[PDB]
Image (cartoon, rainbow, N blue to C red; front, side, top):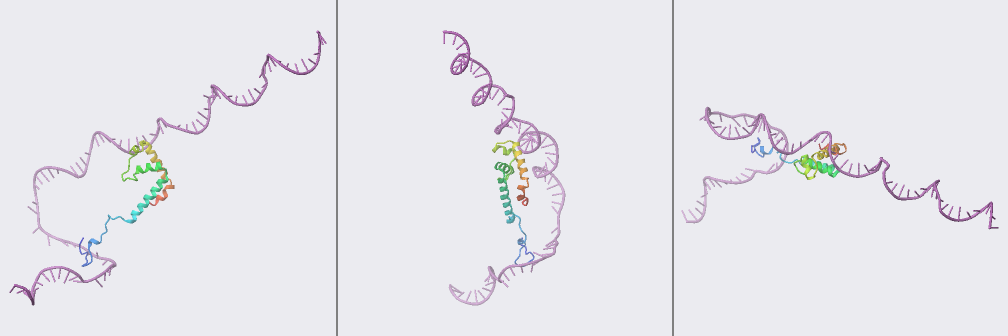
Amino acid sequence: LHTPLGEDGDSEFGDLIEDSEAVVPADAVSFTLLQEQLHSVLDTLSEREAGVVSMRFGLTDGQPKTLDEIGKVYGVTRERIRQIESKTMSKLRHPSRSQVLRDYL
DNA sequence: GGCGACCCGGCGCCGCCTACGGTCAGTACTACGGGTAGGGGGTATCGGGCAACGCGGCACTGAACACCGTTGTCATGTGCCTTG
């Protein structure tokens, strides 16, 4: 990386290649706005529906939880949880609570 | 003998940002040996689709009583007629 870069002075091949680990502020703030808007639309729905979808898709922890995995803290059945998840997906699929999330993809 | 030159070392610098830049370098070899990460099959455990079994309003078997309403009922009282 300390090669002359073909230039006798003031240059180094080590100062011409961009990295990839660096966080792009644009993408980061877009993600933050996505998180806030999704949390807002999530609060718009019922608090119970909100909580169950959040725990299923893991919106507070990195790893999502399985259906029956939610039926221990909340004390519900593996098929009840599936049913409320299904009707949550049905409601969120409504064009009402989709537009604000369309551009986010 | 400390000065003195001189001699050398030795470093250290030589100004600020800007556009593009083109490429390639020669003389071992086999042989074994272990040991694996990858190729396979079969098994134990967790994760989905239909009914599940609650509830609640009210609603009915109306049943069985209750609330007035009513013409049943009547032993017991006025008015006229006959006899004291």
